[PDB]
Image (cartoon, rainbow, N blue to C red; front, side, top):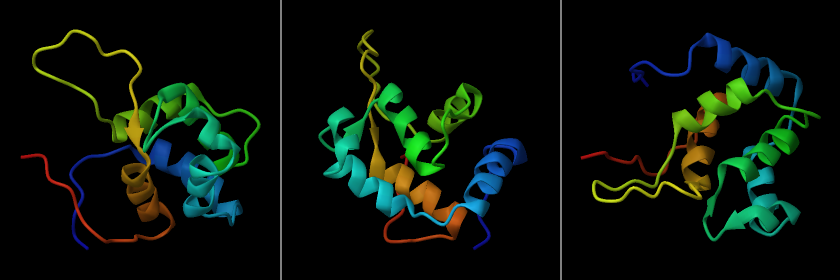
Length: 118
């Protein structure tokens, strides 16, 4: 596992790290929450918006308030929804499976199928 190529500094990883360090929950646990759970009230099919994502960090880190700073670097990590012929970047959703993968690395690393940005 010799990847890496410049990602969220040790500042964001530290926060989330130190955060999950004390926590023992699972991303797959919160995932279902947003799937069938109540958190699914702010999910658009298989993609969730930015705001709705906030709740994730809430339950995820079981925090009572997550920093927008990290939330910003959080979304930047993984996104989706663009076009080289459209000036409407409204209601931006993101794949959970994608975030679930990235996050899976934090806790450890659960492979299954890597993506490709050809």
